[PDB]
Image (tube, rainbow over all chains, first blue to last red; front, side, top):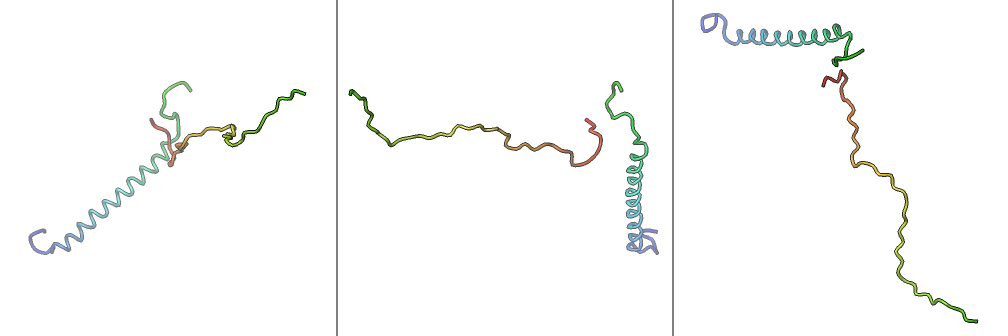
Length: 53
Length: 41
């Protein structure tokens, strides 16, 4: 509805806030998974050397 | 009695106290990790 009639660019850009703002909230949570994924599959062996245990 | 005798000429005397220094580096600065984790490489 951009350029055409109702959306009244600020009321659009108030939503283009909320997309760009809540996709940023995903980037918070998708990294908050990637934090708590590297406390889940982070068990243990080995430490990243390769050799004889 | 033939007595050899010393007349005291006095003034200069460098006094140096030699004594056991225990040398140490100027900045030791042991690299301690600021942040936990596996040492990757």
